[PDB]
Length: 20
Length: 20
Length: 20
Ligand SMILES: *Cc1cc(C*)cc(C*)c1
Image (cartoon, rainbow over all chains, first blue to last red; front, side):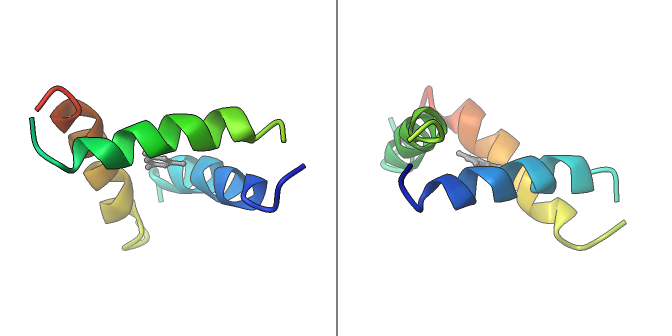
């Protein structure tokens, strides 16, 4: 439940945006 | 053997902490 | 096609460098 979890979510978006 | 390897280790911890 | 894609490329290099 740590706030750092937000960073992980961003990573996922970054990977998807890789095609962008 | 580069010191940057430490960053990779942190990434792993971040992924696990994702459930936190 | 976003410039952020460069960050993703770096991540890949970091993972490989993990053995370094
Ligand atoms: C979340 C994350 C972590 C690492 C080590 C690298 C990338 C691209 C994303």
